[PDB]
Image (tube, rainbow, N blue to C red; front, side):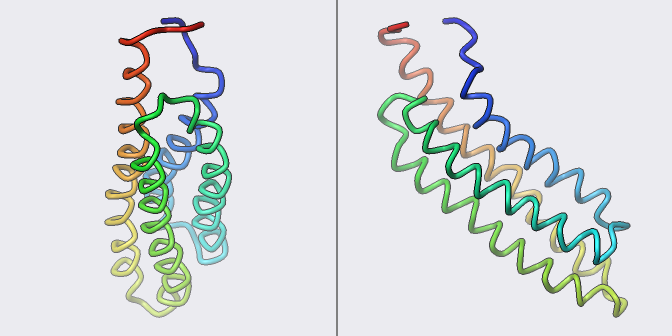
Length: 139
């Protein structure tokens, strides 16, 4: 029952990091221009990429039982992402018009589910990690 925040940190990081941004980005979103936003979102999406790989390393980090769910969760996050990425690709063009705050708001919405999505990700894992704790700790 030590602090195994070694590799679980990398996994728990992306999740948070991306999340912490999902929100923050929302704040600096309104202002964030179409030149600084295009990437902004691109970043969140980029993080996912690495996150996926990170998960693979986390897969084992957790006890057998939170595999499928985890896998299904990955697609879950991406989902919102994909829809989030598109939202941007549009906002980028639906900003110079005038109905920015409108479309921009939409993004926020996802940001809400996103934060959760990312949560439900580890949330499940958290249920696994324990599955190991209260069972038979090896190392």
